[PDB]
Image (spheres, coloured by chain):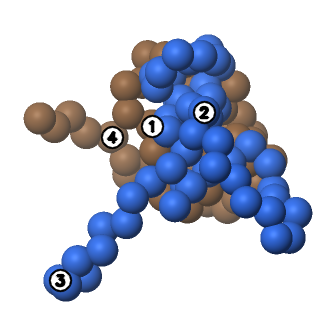
Chain colours: A brown, B blue
Amino acid sequence: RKRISNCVADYSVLYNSASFSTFKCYGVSPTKLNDLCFTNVYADSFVIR
Amino acid sequence: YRLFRKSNLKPFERDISTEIYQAGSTPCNGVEGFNCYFPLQSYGFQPTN
């Protein structure tokens, strides 16, 4: 659980990249993500089946 | 029911077009693919629901 704060969360190289085979946001659209302000962001990473 | 649509309908307007909404960078003109999906979506209506 890594905390992300006081930075810009541009997804120009994240969403546009085809390297991610599964990308789904349950609260907002990726298109409106870039123009939506946020707060402290927690990043959780793991490897599963 | 249509999950997503490029624009916002003016009041009392019906949309039947089933063209594959392309949100991804590549247009996916033929079929789904990179952030390209079928606009319509069915209900999970159930007695258990």
**Residue type (three-letter) at the residue carrying disc 2:** Glu
Going from N to C along the chain, the mark reached first, 2 or 3, is: 2
**Numbered disc 3: secondary structure:** loop
Q: Give the number of the mark in front: 2 or 3.
A: 2
Give the left or right position of residue B12, taking residue A49 as reference. Answer: right
Q: Nearer the viewer, mark 1 or mark 3?
A: 3
Residue extending farthest left: A49
Q: Which residue is mark 3?
A: B48
- For the question of whether residue A37 can be seen, the reply is no
Q: Nearer the viewer, mark 4 or mark 1?
A: 1
x and y, in percent, of residue A39 in the image: 67, 61
Q: Closest to the observer: B41 or A25?
A: B41
Q: Which labelled disc corresponds to residue A45? A: 4
Say what amino acid the circle numbered 3 marks: Thr
Choose the circle earlier in sequence order: 4 or 1. 1
Q: Which mark is residue B19?
A: 2
Please report, as a chain letter, where disc 4 is located. Answer: A
Badge number at residue B39? none
Q: What label does residue A23 carry, if any? A: 1
Marks 1, 2 in one chain: no
Which is more foreground, mark 1 or mark 2? 2
Q: Secondary structure at mark 4?
A: loop
